[PDB]
Length: 92
DNA sequence: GTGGCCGTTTTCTGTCTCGTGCCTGGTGTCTTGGGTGTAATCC
Image (cartoon, rainbow, N blue to C red; front, side, top):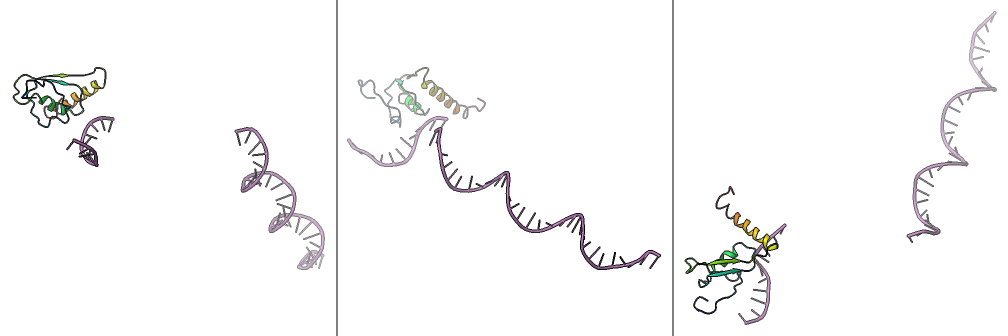
């Protein structure tokens, strides 16, 4: 994927992929389905947002409004707050 | 390219009987009195 001008897109199923695979070639990212682990998505974004990435990277989240996606996304935001007030400011 | 297992995400009238309890008829065991009995003592 990195060393070929063709082979533009490829699906990854971000459970198996994210162990540290180097995919700096990517610049755009599409998230299709929200996951349960709030962590599995940071490695997913890091599949194109490696340290010192060559070009700007963007994330497009898919979210079905008025569905379980709403509950999961709010849950993930709450989980981010959990690790973002325990380690940032316990007054939040 | 074969699978093993763990790891993971969330919070039926009808009639009868069997038994017995209660009512009743009998029956025990007794208490009172009433007379019979003895006492007895006036004179």
